Every structure is written in structure tokens, then in C-alpha cells.
Image (cartoon, coloured by chain):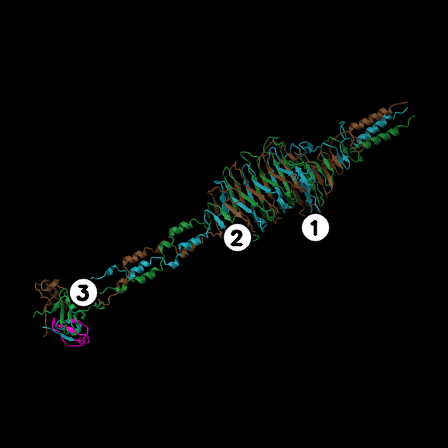
Chain colours: A brown, B green, C cyan
Amino acid sequence: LRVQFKRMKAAEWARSDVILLESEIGFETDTGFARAGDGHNRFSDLGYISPLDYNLLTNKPNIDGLATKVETAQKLQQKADKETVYTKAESKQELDKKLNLKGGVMTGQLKFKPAATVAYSSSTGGAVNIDLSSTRGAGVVVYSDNDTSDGPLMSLRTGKETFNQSALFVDYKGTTNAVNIAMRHATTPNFSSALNITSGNENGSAMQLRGSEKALGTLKITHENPSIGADYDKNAAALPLDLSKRQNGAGTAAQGIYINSTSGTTGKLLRIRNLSDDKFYVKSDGGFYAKETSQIDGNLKLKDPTANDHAATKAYVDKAISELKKLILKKH
Amino acid sequence: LRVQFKRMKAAEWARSDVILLESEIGFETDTGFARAGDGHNRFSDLGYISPLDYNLLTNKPNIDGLATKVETAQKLQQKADKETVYTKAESKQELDKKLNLKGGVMTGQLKFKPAATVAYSSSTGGAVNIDLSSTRGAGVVVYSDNDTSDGPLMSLRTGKETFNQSALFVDYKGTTNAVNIAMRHATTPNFSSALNITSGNENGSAMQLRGSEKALGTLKITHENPSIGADYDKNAAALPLDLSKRQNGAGTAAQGIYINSTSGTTGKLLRIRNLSDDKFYVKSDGGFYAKETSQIDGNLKLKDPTANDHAATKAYVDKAISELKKLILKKH
Amino acid sequence: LRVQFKRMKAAEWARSDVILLESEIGFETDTGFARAGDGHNRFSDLGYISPLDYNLLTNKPNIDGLATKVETAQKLQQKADKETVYTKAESKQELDKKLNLKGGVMTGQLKFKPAATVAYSSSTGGAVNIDLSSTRGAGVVVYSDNDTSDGPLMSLRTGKETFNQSALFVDYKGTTNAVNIAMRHATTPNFSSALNITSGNENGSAMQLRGSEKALGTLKITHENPSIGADYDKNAAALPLDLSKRQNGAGTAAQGIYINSTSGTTGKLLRIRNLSDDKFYVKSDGGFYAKETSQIDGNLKLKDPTANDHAATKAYVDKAISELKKLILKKH
């Protein structure tokens, strides 16, 4: 036999009242599908003659091997966005603008404005502290090979009249010179000074100097001729003082050189020699000594003579003259 | 006809011995599915009357377009976790705490403790090296407008007695003053000094000074009256020395002023003038000159007179007196 | 009945000319599947007797819940690769090599080579600017407790002969000493100096000093015996000058001490005292005073006597002698 089954379009069955007997097959002509009845339900409620369940399929894929939207998002949440992170290059770029501890080159100004913890006292104080105890190099080196400038190499300035510290303070222990100033014998000459000092304070000495030398001068001044010409430096002097009055003032009464010995000295107060030969000196007691002929454009007030080599007085002459006068006048 | 087929529950077939002929259909009443026999196999081993193969389905999805767990994880492995990376903000935060090469403001102390490569010698040495050869600004500028402080602006200190370098060393070439110290004429006066120097070393001069001036003083001291009152500075002096003994000592024999010329000079060793007029001077040979009347509270030991204007001696008077005595005494 | 259907292998149907009537079932013996005809199409073009449409399956999975390759890649594109980002550790590593503004420790050299904006003038200039107006600490502190070294603590050097600024410049307002130099009384003695100054410039004074003291010395020199032995410092002096010629030169004519008062002074130009007692002095007018007996190894040229206590001249003696001679000679 060639069996044919109850048949009509899917659309047609869906509204038909035909009840297929149990296991009787129904055929959807427009789809080609079929359904079997259970003897009581209408076509549209029967099920197809073969499974339609995903769990029953063969060759299914690996669904569990696939990533879920949620799963991925959770993981992506832990990852850093490009926009909120610097690239190694950008980091390098910003780091190269910073100074290394190992050292570097500043091209701008470095200002110091200390909060000041307590800023100490002694060998660990200072905005800038340099300890050279373990190296043999220099501490601060400042130089200029420029033809001119509008400022000094180093400048120290205090402002208040109550400032109770020093500008510069040197505590020195060693075998050489503490402060060494050397003004190179210039090329284009100038009328300057190696060290220039000015004080407007009237109650304190411009410069104070105390030494405890055994066989030297506290202050040793040495002038050396700048020429080989015997009398080139005939205007020079090792030490020249000037006592001058004030700007539109009335005058001055200051003294030139004041020598004193508050505790009493034994030596000579003023000793003047040439080629290491005493030529003039003022002993500690006041008596002076002069090696060569001298001159006074005035009179000399002194004690009468007692020795044959003493300068004689008017009174001494007039007395000897008078006595001779009396002596001689006997007459006849 | 209304064909009905061999039928029983899925559970029932699974254990039945009924062998469906080839192509004969079997019907599962509780599921509604059917299977056709191959003429030898039991129901449970037949297959459904329609495919159950995922590869055969229509409208399948895009399985290959879906991401695999493995695939994603491999990619996520290359990505940087949030927890192990600084955000641009955090980076900025840490970078702003660092000093720029362009310059900045230090608010704390900067200590230097040089490893010391060799720390050089000359114009590239120093923990801090400042080269002002191409700019016109200052090098180191240190100032304080505070009313007081517990420390100095700049302090240099060496510790060992064998230290063979100087605290401060100035090598100067230029047209102005190498070191310029200026102590402003104070407001609240003090009994200080612009420059104060003290040496405890007995084998070396407190201060050494050498110059090669053509027409000046190596050391030029100038005192200017602080007042317009003619005799306000009657106690002052340009230069005052003091020769004092030690703490609970026995005395001192030091000399005040020592002038010498080891190579022999032509000039005047001591020249004292007023208004640029010679008033007193000690020639190079020792002879002195005095412009006005003088006084000696004692005797003067000198050579006999040869000129009519020479101070005469005792011996000269007594001789002329004696000769006149003899001369006169003839008598009768 | 036991119905059997038209049947043959899938391979066999695919090339058969058999036309199954509408709803007549065909059976693939090698697969076990079946197809129903539509009365005109060949077997291979009929469809299976049950759906094969993914949309129709039950228990489908959550396909939309799965992540797409595209979707993931787009998201991963925003994330930062490990290879192009520094880890917090690497960042810390590089940041710890940089100096903090709060301060730190330099272990290398810090060079300054100012672009120089204009580098100012006054209290904000300098490569290094230190403002201590709000703290009581030190500014620059430089010390060395090393036994020796090959360089100085601080060194300033200018190169051109046209340099128109000073090496070091101190502007000081306060109650103490501007520059304070102290050379500790050495352990291993040396033949140095606290301050050593040398000038090769012939047109300017080695050292210039100006003060406006009311009752002091501009320059105050004090020598204190280093011993308690009364005559230990019998070679010393507070101030010793030396006038020397040049290297293989001809001689020198320089002067020792030059005292002048360009504006005219009232005081004593040279005052020498012992225990605060005048022993010798040269008045402003040139007349000198000597407390004790003196000596001249030569002659003294002076004015004739007018007072009984004036040193008498040759001429005065010879005149009084002559007058007595005439006077006496009357005879008989």
C-alpha cells in the first residue's frame, strides 16, 4: 500500500476540531512536518514526531568553553584602562625632568625656604649641608669666565639691626691658610682692592685682629716693588693712614696711630730698621734712638746736662758763663 | 484508513522484546516520539525518525563568533592589573614631590655626602659646582631678614690639625673688589666688628698681607669722623695696637710696630703728614725730622757740634769755657 | 497491520526517480530517517518529517549571554598592556633615585649651568638662593673632619680681566661680627696665617679699610703672649712691615708707614703709650714728645735757645763766649 495521512496546512490544523487517534499521524502539507495524536488533544497541542530538545542533539558544540558577558566583564574590571595610566615612555619623560640623587645639572634656580624643624645648631644644620669628611674634593665651587656680569659670585645679606649672627664664620684647624685671597696681577689694570672693608658703626672697630705669635707679627705687611726699576715705587708705602672729616662737617680730631700695652710690655714700642739694622726706635720707657743726624725746625726743651755727651741747655751755658765772669773778675 | 501503531511508554519499550520490522514505526505514548526498526534491534537501540544532529540544524547561531574562555584568558594575561599600577594622578602626586632640573623650592635640608669618584681638582670639582660663565646673575645668594637666629649665614669648619687645604680660597681677576665687606651704619648700635680675626697659632701670623703697589699703600686705612662736631672723635685712631700678656701669666716683651726692609729701601721708613705737609719723618738712614718745637723729659746723648746750628754738648761748652779761661789768664 | 514503507539507502534515494505521494512516507534504511513527499518532488529535495530549526529547540542555551570575539576585543583595546607600563614597584624604584623637595642626601655632584632668564638683581637672584628670613638655622654649612684633602672647602674664581663684580660680597646689618675668622690654636703647629692676602695689581691697594669710629681704632691689633714666660715673645710684634724689591730687580724706594690727614686733624698723629702712660708722641703740628733720656748717633740741627730749658746751639755758645771775651778785655 501507499499510505496517505490526514493532511492540511499548518494554518488549517491549528484551527481544526479533528482529533487524531493515539499514534495516528497528521501531516502539515506546507511545512512537511507531522504530529501524532494522543487521542484527546487538538492538532496544535500535539508535539512533533521527533525530539526538539537541545540536550538531545549530537555534535553539540562546547558551550561551556565559551566566555560569558558577565565573566569577562568581571575580569576586565580588574584591568587598568589605557587612559588612566602613563606609558613607560611618558614615565621616562617625566622622570628625566627630575634631579637624581647621584647628581645632575640644574638649569634653573634652586630656592631654599626652610620650614625649619629646629634647623639644628652645629655640624648638621643649614639648608645646604656639605660633609667632606670622607672625600678629598672641594665643597662649594663657584666660578665665572664671563667678561662681565650684573652680580657677584657669592653674596650674603642680613637685614635687621638686631641680627645676632655673623654673615660668614670660619672655624679653622689645619696646616695652611684659613682664608686665602689672591688678586692676580691684572691685565687691564684697575684701581680696586683685593679686600675692601667699610664700617659705618661708630661704637665698634671696622676690623679686629688678635694673635698670639711667638716670633712674628700679628699682622705682617709686605710691599714688593712691581718693577725692577730701583725708584719706580717711590710713592708707595706698606701702610698709609688718612684721617678725614665727615661730608660737609666741621673737622676731625682723630689720632693716627695709637700704641698701648695695657698689661705693660718689655719690648720696643716702635722699632724701625733698614737691611736689618736698627735706625730708629722708641724704647718701652719712652726714650728714643736715632742712628743719624737729625733736624728740628724749632726748639728742644730738655733736662740740664750731667754727662759730657749730653745736649746742653741754655741755662747750663749762661751758668758756666756767669761763673767764669765772677771767677775772672778779681782785678788788680 | 486511520492507522495506529505498536505503542507503549518509553519506559515500557526500553525493556520490551518486540522487534519492529524494517521501516515499521513504533510510538512512545508518553513522549509522543516514534522510532522505526531495522528488523533486528530492540526499541531502545533504534534511533528517532528524524535527525538529532547539531550540524544539521538551521538558523544555527554564530558559535565561532563567540569568545572562548581560553582565548580570553590568554589575552587578559597581557593586560596590567589595576592593583599593580599607579594612576596618572598617583604618578603626578609622587612626581610633584620631586625637584625639577629647571629649578624649584626646597623646603627641607639638602645634605651632601660625596662618594667621591675622584672629585677632581679645578673648575669642575666640588659637591656643588656653579658655572656662571654664560649668565650675568649671582652664584650663591644667602640672606636673612629675621630679627635673630641661632646660626650664621654661612659657616666653614675643618676638624683635623693636619688639614692641608684652606677654608675659603679666592682667586680673582677683574676690575672691582675681590671680597667686599660692608657693615651698614647700624640702627641699634653695637660693639662689634665688620671683620674679626683670632689666631692661637704662635708659629704663624694672624694675618698676612702682600701687595705690589706703584703709588699706593698695601694696606690703606681711612677713618672718617662719624659726626660733624669738630672734636667728636678725639678718642678714635686709625690704628691702635695693644700688647697684652696671657691669662694669669707673668708678662710680655712683644714689640709694637716693627718696620724693616730686608732688601734695603730708598724711601722714608716713617712719614707723618698733616694736610699733606710733612711734620715728622724718619729717613731711611735713621735721621729724623721734626717740624715744630719738641720736648724730652730727660737727657739727650749726641755728637759734638760742627755747624753753627747744631745742638751743642756739655763737653763743647766746658771746652770753650776752659780755653777762654786759659786765654784770659795772662795777668799783669 | 504492520506497515512497511518504500525504502532504500540515503545514497539510493538521492538518485531515484520515485515520487512519493503527498504525505506518503519514505524511509532511509542506513540512517533510519524518513521523509514525506509533496507529490511532485524527488526524495533528495523533500525535508525530514520533523523540524531541524535551531529556533524551535527546547532547553536552548543562553547564547546572548556569551561574549563575542568582537565585543571582547573592543573592550580589551581600552586596557593597558603589561609590557608598556611600569609596575608600582618599578615606579618606586625609579622615584627613589630622585631628590625630594622636602630634602634628601646627594651622593654625587650637583652642577649649575644657568640658562639665565635674567637671573635678577637683588634678593631673589643666584643659581642657589637661600632665604632664612623665617627660620633660625644656618644657610650654607661646609665642614671636613678628614685628615687631608686635595681641595678647599669653598673656592671662588673669576677668569676675565674685565670682570666687573666681586667674588664675595657681604652687606651686613646686625649686633655681632659680619665675618668671623678663628684659627684654633693648633695641635701640630704650622707657619700659616688665618687670613692671607696677595695682590699683584700695582694700581690699587691690596687691602682697603674705612671706618667711622667715635672712640676706637678703625683697625685694632692685639697681640697676646702665647706663654706665661715673661720674655717668651721678645721677637714678636703686633705689626711688622717689610719693604722688599722684585725678583732679580734693582731695588725699591717704597715708604714704610705713611700717615696723612687730607682734611686736617686735631689729634696726635702718632701716640705711643705703655701701661696707659704717654711715653712718646708726635703732635699734629709736628712737635714730638719723649718721656725718657734719648740718643742720637749724629748731630742735631735746631733753632737757637730762647728759654732757659732749651737745648742750646753752637752759635749760641760761641756768641756768649765772644761777648764775654770782649767784655772782659778792658785791661789796666
Could you give the CA–CA distance between mark 1 and mark 2, rounded to whole angstroms?
A: 47 Å
| SS for callout 2 | loop
Question: Are discs 1 and 2 located on one and the same chain?
Answer: no
User: Which of B230 and B148 lies nearest the eye of the viewer?
Assistant: B148
Q: Which residue is mark 2?
A: B115
Q: Which residues are magenta?
A: C8-34
Residue C121 located left or right of residue B251: left
Q: Residue furthest right?
A: B332
Query: Residue at label 1?
Result: C248
Q: Is residue A190 visible?
A: yes
Does B121 sit above or below residue A297? Answer: below
Label 3 secondary element? loop
The answer to whether A316 appears left or right of C143 in the picture is: right
Res. A152 in view: no
Type of amino acid under label 2: Ala
Calculate the distance from the C-alpha at mark 2 to the C-alpha at mark 3. 84 Å
> What's the CA distance linking mark 1 and mark 3?
127 Å
Q: Which mark is residue B28?
A: none
Q: Position of residue B306 (x, y in %)?
A: 81, 35
- In the image, which is nearer the foreground, mark 2 or mark 3? 3
Left-right relation of C45 to A241: left
Chain label for disc 3: A
Q: Which residue in the structure is indicated by mark 3?
A: A52
Q: Is residue A159 above or below residue C317?
A: below
